[PDB]
Image (cartoon, helix red, strand yellow):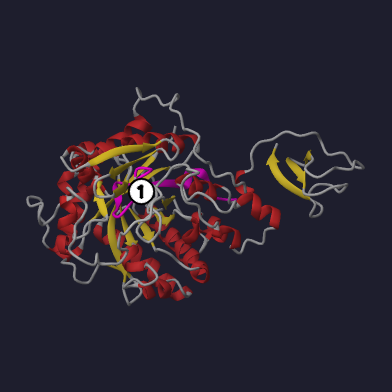
Amino acid sequence: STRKAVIGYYFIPTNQINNYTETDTSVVPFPVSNITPAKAKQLTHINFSFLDINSNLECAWDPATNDAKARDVVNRLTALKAHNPSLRIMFSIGGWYYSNDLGVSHANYVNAVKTPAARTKFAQSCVRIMKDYGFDGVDIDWEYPQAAEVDGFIAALQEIRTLLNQQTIADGRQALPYQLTIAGAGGAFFLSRYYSKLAQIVAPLDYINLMTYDLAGPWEKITNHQAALFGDAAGPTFYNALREANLGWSWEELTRAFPSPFSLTVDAAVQQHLMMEGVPSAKIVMGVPFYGRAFKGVSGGNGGQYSSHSTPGEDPYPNADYWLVGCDECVRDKDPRIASYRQLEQMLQGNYGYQRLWNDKTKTPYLYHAQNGLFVTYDDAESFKYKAKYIKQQQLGGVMFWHLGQDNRNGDLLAALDRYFNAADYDDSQLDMGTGLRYTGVGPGNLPIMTAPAYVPGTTYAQGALVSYQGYVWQTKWGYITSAPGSDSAWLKVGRL
């Protein structure tokens, strides 16, 4: 049917733009020329990252950027469209460094969306940047607007959408219209900031790209998979912050939607979006990491899973002990806590002491270094089989990943995703999704189809009785009930006919 989106970040820091070269990996590890025609054909979107919002409350490049070299880099990316008439070169505003609560530019995000006049100036600057540099759409990665800033954020997205639609008409771009996306939270704590207004946030978007990764990290006391598809009962659980969001729902409604504690998984984030009325599955994009998160000081017993650890959480990494054995990129980047898939393959292939293990519940791989007590959570072409099947079963919009430079040299992870979506001779009908824990929540937007006897006036219904009435299946919350379903508080709408 409709092609699944495959959205890959291209991240390049300012110093690499300013010294851009395609022939020295010690200066630019991943130049645009490494995105071969074959890789360009497997992508639908490249998110060029990151631009910012400046103190003038406009979308802007880092002011240290050499503009001529920035245009040259973007021009190399948009040249790739010659190989793929569906490909878009988006640009992303924000990211964690610029826009987190304590980030260097955070107040500019708050202020840019705060008033109608600020939103107009900001929205215009986004489309002006898009047109000036030749980008194909706008991606906003504010991590994350707080509950009080959400209305301004929503209005800013609405205003950008209108201006993008004007631009599509002006440029005759109906065959490849300018798009608007966001990187959205992939876990319930950050998601709770704007969850109650999710439908308004998603309405002006082509896609909401869920950051369904970093669900574990050195900031948690217990090692865990950072992007488990489904839950492992042996693993940690978390409070479900969504049950405290300002939804106006009843106790039964909140309880049915937000089991707590729950397993912090990719499936949980996807289902949490689908539960909200007005959030269509086709706009939800599943983020996946092309990197692993490494932990030290772990115990044995379960391959390093669910163990205490001694991994520093600070930025920058606080000393020069690059303890992730074999991770040469970690030495370059002065941080042993993140390793690209590219590097992880080499670490497993070399004489470095890792064993690749597989969790059949989470459907994700992990490395365990038994001698030194290291644990690495990552994703690979095998975990992507299950995530791709989930994307197709749940009718999601596609996949997003951070980032292109972390795929291996041959682009095997990107090629795998493209294969699972598009290869005629790939068959996952028999791929077993396992018995990992599913997120069981149901909300107004994902009522299951059900059948039940028609409601009968005058009948006294005990607690838990199910009836069909006026298009839906309803359940009594207590007994005995005689009211018509929907006329009072006694009936829970549990399914659709």
Task: Tell whether 489 sits left or right of 406.
Answer: right
Question: From what the image shows, is residue 121 above or below residue 385?
Answer: below
Q: Position of residue 25 (x, y in %)?
A: 10, 51
Relative to 170, say whether 44 is above or below. above
Where is residue 386? Give x, y as percent: 41, 35
Q: Is residue 283 left or right of residue 310?
A: right
- The residue under the point 28% across, 50% down is 373
Outermost residue on the left side: it is 23
Q: Looking at this rendering, what residue extends furthest in the right direction?
A: 458
Displayed quadrant of residue 391:
top left
Reading the image, the residue beneath label 1 is 173
Which residues are drawn in magenta? 277-303
Crowding near the residue tagged with mark 1, few <14, some 14–19, many ≥20 C-alpha atoms within 10 Å: few
Q: Residue visible at 58% across and 62% down?
A: 245
The location of residue 295, given as percent across then percent down, is: 30, 53
Is the residue 246 above or below the residue 495 in the image?
below
Q: Position of residue 37 (x, y in %)?
A: 20, 38
- Asked if the magenta segment contains residue 448, the reply would be no
Quadrant of image for the C terminus: top right
Q: Is residue 123 visible?
A: yes
Element at badge 1? loop
Amino acid beneath label 1? Arg
Residue 46 in sight in this render: no
